[PDB]
Length: 333
Image 1 (cartoon, helix red, strand yellow):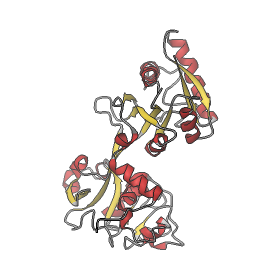
Image 2 (cartoon, helix red, strand yellow):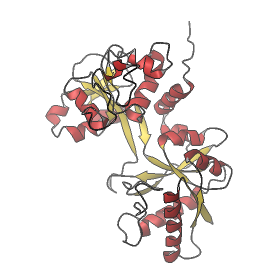
Image 3 (cartoon, helix red, strand yellow):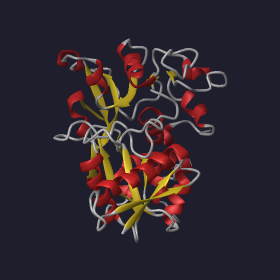
Image 4 (cartoon, one colour):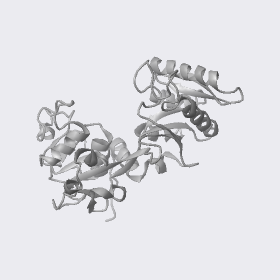
């Protein structure tokens, strides 16, 4: 049976046809094959898949969630792995690095100074805010408003530092570029190192990539979700949420997960990470990151029948929800 791969552009459309043709030249007729389909956008793809016109798209976590909602109802089926092949990571933890003994837990950020990677970025803004959401002072609209009104200043690269200058206190000008030394994953970490902030919202490996010695990383801690703080080495049992990088999705009912996975692993075997020079599953002279990320090392089948909510995780889903639906429920008394 064939697999109809959805592409969200012409550079992606070409790589797909080139990805199709390729399998042909090397795989036997009895084998799984690729059909190419072009839609205007991630979502269209998510819909053309729902409506049985395409079979798979690869999405970032955020779109994994939408792709699942009704009436698109798409499940995550094949994960894209990075790192090695022995200890291959497919997710990345989103954490909240602070300073050893800086006294305060997750339920105490109000008033403190925050260091983010980018307004809009998942681990730096999307997750930490979503979770905290119902603590940002109403009016919670706009969001740039309420967050400027919760931390006694921050650095939110790409924030409306004009209408909310507060947010650029720790990095004036709100430079949405590396020119801003506090910009991004490592900048946001430094914003903490210099003590320019109180909390630095980053991904787990960040501290490891920014301090080469235990003795110094020993000087930092992580804000566990349970009003506790564990050492930097324990992000797995102390992280704000769990996030899978890229994910091929298929329909829940109908799916083709059997065949997709097949066509993928066969393709990584032939066309994978340096298995030839005559085409490249993770690279294209047509542009960077078309179809599958160029950083990817291959693929991992995901847990049989597991839906986006369990795949993404309680925290992420809670965050995205709050950010989207923006409604803190009423309570007990």
